[PDB]
Image (cartoon, rainbow, N blue to C red):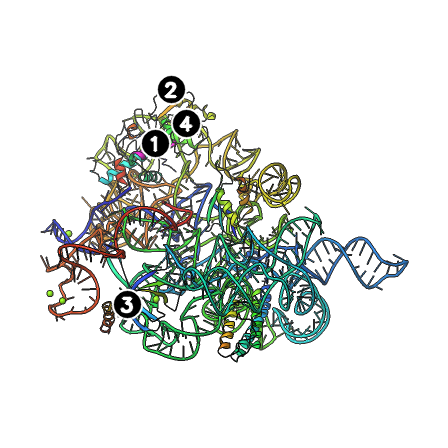
Amino acid sequence: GRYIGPVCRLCRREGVKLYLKGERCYSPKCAMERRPYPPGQHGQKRARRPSDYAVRLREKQKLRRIYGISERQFRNLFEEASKKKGVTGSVFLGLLESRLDNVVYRLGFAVSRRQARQLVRHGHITVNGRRVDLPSYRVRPGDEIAVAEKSRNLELIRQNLEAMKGRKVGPWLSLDVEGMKGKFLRLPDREDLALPVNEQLVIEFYSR
Amino acid sequence: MVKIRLARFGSKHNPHYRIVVTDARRKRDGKYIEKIGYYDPRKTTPDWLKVDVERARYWLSVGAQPTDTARRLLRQAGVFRQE
Amino acid sequence: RNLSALKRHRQSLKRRLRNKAKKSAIKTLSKKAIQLAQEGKAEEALKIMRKAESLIDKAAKGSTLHKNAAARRKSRLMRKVRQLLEAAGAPLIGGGLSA
Amino acid sequence: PKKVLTGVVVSDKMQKTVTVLVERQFPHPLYGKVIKRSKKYLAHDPEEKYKLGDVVEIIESRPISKRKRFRVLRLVESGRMDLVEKYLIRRQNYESLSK
RNA sequence: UGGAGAGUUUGAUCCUGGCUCAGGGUGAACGCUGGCGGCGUGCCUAAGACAUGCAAGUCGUGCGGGCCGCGGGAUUUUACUCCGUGGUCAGCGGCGGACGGGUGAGUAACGCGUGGGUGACCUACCCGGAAGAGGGGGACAACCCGGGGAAACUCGGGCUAAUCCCCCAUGUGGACCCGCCCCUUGGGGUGUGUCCAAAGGGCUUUGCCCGCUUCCGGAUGGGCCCGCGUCCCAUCAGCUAGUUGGUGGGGUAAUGGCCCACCAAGGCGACGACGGGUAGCCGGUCUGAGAGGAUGGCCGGCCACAGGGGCACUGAGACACGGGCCCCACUCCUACGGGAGGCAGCAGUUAGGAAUCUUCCGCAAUGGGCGCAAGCCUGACGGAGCGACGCCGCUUGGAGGAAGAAGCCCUUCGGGGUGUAAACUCCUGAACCCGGGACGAAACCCCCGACGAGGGGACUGACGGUACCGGGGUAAUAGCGCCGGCCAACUCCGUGCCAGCAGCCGCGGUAAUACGGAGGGCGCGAGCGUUACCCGGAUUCACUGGGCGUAAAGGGCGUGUAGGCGGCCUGGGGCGUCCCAUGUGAAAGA
Ligand SMILES: [Mg+2]
Ligand SMILES: [Mg+2]
Ligand SMILES: [Mg+2]
Ligand SMILES: [Mg+2]
Ligand SMILES: [Mg+2]
Ligand SMILES: [Mg+2]
């Protein structure tokens, strides 16, 4: 099951701060502030002109590591998008973005995808009333991703729903803050996300 | 003797039958002469039962005994109901 | 190690017996008819052939010879008898043939 | 429909029967070229009426023999000893093809 | 909506050319590792051998008995006997045992695939229609009495019923000879002549039901014929006496040298006959940009086989896996004369093998067989069990947390790394405990109605006390491969052409990013590696898509056989070729 181990640690290695640790990876350190380089004995050593493979690799790692999903699962999603009608890279970002464990986090019910996953497994989240505990669930457009009435009380739901009192929400989403529930309006366009990752190198990574 | 009767499709703990005509001597999930409906015993769909009834009447007309449960379902969509 | 529908073997033997029997008599009769006809014979030739006829049909009733296996034998026999008959003289006792 | 083939008579050296060579041409399954291919059929001739060099139609039939399954339907044209000759050399060619 | 290339011949270059890798795939096996569940799938080898249990029956509404019971009767004497009823056993008679299940040995062939023929044919049960069922006679088991055998069993004698068997009649009709008419292979029709039917049972008993006989039809299933397609070797080139055709017979449901007598001298072959090797074929599966290559496990269709080889009987169907006969091999019983037997059904045992499961629950569901029904049978099937064998889902925590603990690795001795990683603070609560708890199942059947239509009613869950719901509630598993280039990831020790690595180029001879250990890093993650096999890259058999002066490759030269190819103009035909309709192209798969 999914990654598990040192993390704002590729808030290093991939070269760019990935948002993985949530509230800290925001505040003098996704260690990227304190150490903007690769991990281990050789981290700050003279860089090496890397291969058009090494390049393509890294990029797909990056994207995959953001959303926390595995290579097995990732690779399939992609496969599915090539056979699908339309420009392929976007579509994939689309499907990637339509995963419950991430919509929940996009609505700020949790501060981390890692944390937002645990809310889905552990019950605390619903899809149009009915309770849903698969982080991989494909939210389609028109769905309502609510908090569990029985879970509203929890210190963590409250503290987090609270910091969203002011905050803005994605163009393809909405958010009734005091009813502790939101809405997947449509699937986002490449333009709508500002992801630190050139998608066409991913396509190209899987063409050999 | 030729039969109207139920062939098991679907999967495990997911029965789904196809109401088929066939020669009686063929295995159950083997080659049928004609599909004429389907049936979901768990009614997990609003449309869990359906029957081309002009065709049912056809075969009945050329002699085809239905299983007993083939005929129950045939009735529900009034294959035998007159006037 | 004892399957009581070996009853089917008992029966078969009986029908074999019954069957063999009717057959044997259709031959020894048909043979006898064509013979008398290769000799120019009114009554005696057809009389037999017409006994032979019956016997065939009779055997067709059951599982013996059923069908048109029947017919075949009637055709072959009552062709032959007639042929041989004009291959000499006499045509008489009307018996079996549409003269 | 009972297949009708047309070819040439290349043998009447058999009683009530003729060997009828039938050609056929087509695209080659992989290599494009139109190739020819040919076949003798033994066709039934009850009135030994056709003979050497007749071009004849040929029809699917109820089996007459082991390997007669066609009947001579009609004459198309007489003569054609060229085609017959053409055949006959190809046959006599095989003589100095041995060891 | 589709196509990537790299390493390696030289001191260097270009080219040719082979090898090798990166990707997908599998009924896999093997190493280390291993938490949960769902859906799949699991003897590829010896078509070797098999212990034990189950896998095909059912019908008393076809018939007569035996054996163990109960009840009532004839007599007022208990012997003898008539009737009724319950067990239970087989027998006779019917239907089923030709389906369902297994397996791929054989088979290069009308076996399969595809499209057609059948004027050359058959089809039990089912449906529609027409017309019938009036008399008589017989036997063989059961049962009883003998005799032979050790056993399997067997031979004789006597009695008997029926939906068992025969005779005679009635002939809606149908069969055959002959003739005539239509049609055109043996299809319809028709006239004399001959020939051929039947069975009874149950009652809610004169009016129904389950059946019976003859005929024409329908439906479904199948037989035989034909065109085209169907691997390798020409270091297999000539093959053939039922052989090719004829006439006439037999045989069959039916064509045909299928078989037989007689006549004739024919048939096949470089367009590959004959011979040898290999193989069940297809829907489809995998791979590929495609063309194509490879493949035919599972599921579905057709074939063949049932220890090896013959044969027939019964029957609508068989030349029959759990029917029969004989020969061969093999195992067992044997009183040595003789018998018995056949898991390529489900389990399971053994043997070969790198490798392939439970002697499980249920007939509750679907399907099948017999029965009027109730029901009985079904290792078909529906489920559970075992394998990470495959695919999918999910857990081993979440948020805080130092200019950063300890330990371990480097160190130009300042420091750098593991590392927010742990510690520890709050949070959630896989597992586990409690409570409740399914759908899958409404029919058949009974009651109203009319045995219809329609209405009503009841019985029935193997999976299972499972899924799912509610309540409580514990921080609670991580491994494997790799870091010389191709290919993503580097440093210290150890070791010295040793020990060892290695897919290919190639690493190791005291400073090794290539060996072995460390730390660290890269990639995947309940997996990760390895070996084998397939397509790929390989335009490296080149149709798409290659070549031959010197790289592999022009025959030593002619002559010419077959074959391939063929100038200008016109015309006919319409085989090639093109277009439109229409049929076929099953379902599953994509
Ligand atoms: Mg060199
Ligand atoms: Mg061969
Ligand atoms: Mg190594
Ligand atoms: Mg190729
Ligand atoms: Mg030269
Ligand atoms: Mg020349």
Distance from label 4 to label 3 (Cα)? 87 Å
- The reply to whether the magenta stretch includes residue C14 is no
Q: Helix or strand or loop: what does disc 3 sit on?
A: loop
Where is residue E147, by image quadrant? bottom right
Q: Nearer the viewer, mark 3 or mark 1?
A: 3
The residue labelled by disc 4 is A144
Q: Is residue A93 magenta?
A: yes
Query: Which mark lies nearer to you, 4 or 3?
Result: 3
- Determine which residue is flagged by label 2: A165
**Nearer to us: label 4 or label 2:** 4
Residue of label 3: D54
Q: Using the image as rendered, state which of residue E187 and residue E161 is in the foreground.
A: E187
Point out residue E544 in the picture as x, y percentages from the top left corner: 22, 51
Instruction: Please check whether the numbered discs 3 and 1 fall on a single chain.
Output: no
The residue type indicated by label 4 comes to Glu
Q: Is residue E525 above or below residue E403?
A: below
Chain where mark 1 sits: A
Q: CA distance from mark 4 to mark 1?
A: 15 Å
Q: Earlier in the sequence, mark 4 or mark 1?
A: 1
- Per the picture, the main secondary structure of the magenta-coloured stretch is helix
Q: Chain of mark 2?
A: A
Name the residue carrying label 1: A97
Name the secondary structure under disc 4: loop
Q: Are marks 3 and 2 on the same chain?
A: no
Which amino acid type is marked by label 1?
Glu
Q: Secondary structure at mark 1?
A: helix
Q: Mark 2 or mark 1, which is nearer the start of the sequence?
A: 1
Dot in front, 1 or 2: 1
Q: Tell me residue E45's x, y (percent).
A: 40, 61
Residue A104 falls left or right of residue C78: left
- Quadrant of the rendering where the C terminus of chain A is positioned: top left
Region of the chain picked out in magenta, as a range: A90-100
